[PDB]
């Protein structure tokens, strides 16, 4: 039942400035730990550097809030 | 291991305007559900009515964020 933990990931990520939705989220248990990969939407007119900053902020916010996550890979794609 | 869920309760409650710490928190599992009681600190010069409003806001915020909670009793005491 991954719904609860994935809902928490999505909520945490959406609250980070510059996130235009969670496009993709894959999470899996590795023992009691979560390993996850996610794609966030960002403003197509943000720079590549800004998108990298948003990704890093999402990684921090999500790992900060969901303590069981032991790996979180975040990438960005243009949305709207 | 109640630490993770109790940390989440405390954090959620502290982010509600007017909460001056969590004085007490007791949480227990009733099957897969959490039942909890908590005491929040509030400004001694808030009115009784305001303290009741803060308690209700904490109940909403905490239940909103921690979906496994199926009962949450919140009371208030003067702090500082």
Image (cartoon, coloured by chain):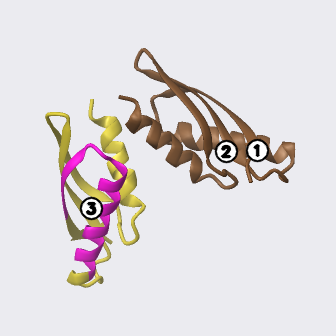
Chain colours: A yellow, B brown
In the image as oriented, which residue stretches furthest toward the top? B31
Measuring from the top left, give residue B61's x and y in whole percent. Answer: 58, 44
For disc 3, the neighbor class at 10 Å (few under 14, some 14 to 19, many from 20) is many
Residue receiving disc 3: A59
Image point (63%, 38%), residue name: B59
Residue A29 numbered tag = none
Q: Quadrant of the C terminus of chain B?
A: bottom right
Residue receiving disc 1: B53
Q: In the rendered structure, which segment of residues is drawn in magenta?
A: A50-74
Q: In the figure, residue A29 lies in which quadrant? A: top left
**Considering depth in this image, is B18 or A19 the residue closer to the camera?**
B18
Side of A21 relative to B67 (left or right): left
Above/below status of A1 relative to B17: above
Above/below status of A9 relative to A54: above
Image point (27%, 29%), residue name: A1
What separation in Å lies between label 1 and label 2 (alpha carbons)?
Answer: 6 Å
Above/below status of B57 relative to A78: above
Co-location on one chain, circles 3 and 2: no
Co-location on one chain, circles 3 and 1: no
Co-location on one chain, circles 1 and 2: yes
For disc 2, the neighbor class at 10 Å (few under 14, some 14 to 19, many from 20) is some
Residue receiving disc 2: B57
Chain of the residue under the numbered disc 3 shown in the image: A
Numbered circles on residues, count = 3
**Considering depth in this image, is A41 or A5 the residue closer to the camera?**
A5
Residue A47, magenta (yes or no): no
Asked if disc 3 and disc 2 are in contact, CB closer than 8 Å, the reply is no
């Amino acid at each position: 039942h991954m719904e609860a933990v994935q809902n928490r990931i999505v909520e945490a990520a959406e609250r980070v400035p510059g996130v235009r939705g969670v496009i993709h989220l894959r999470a899996r248990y590795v023992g009691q730990d979560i390993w996850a990969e996610m794609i966030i939407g960002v403003d197509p007119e943000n720079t590549v550097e800004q998108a990298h900053e948003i990704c890093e902020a999402v990684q921090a916010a999500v790992c900060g809030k969901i303590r069981r996550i032991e790996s979180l890979h975040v990438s960005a794609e243009a949305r709207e």
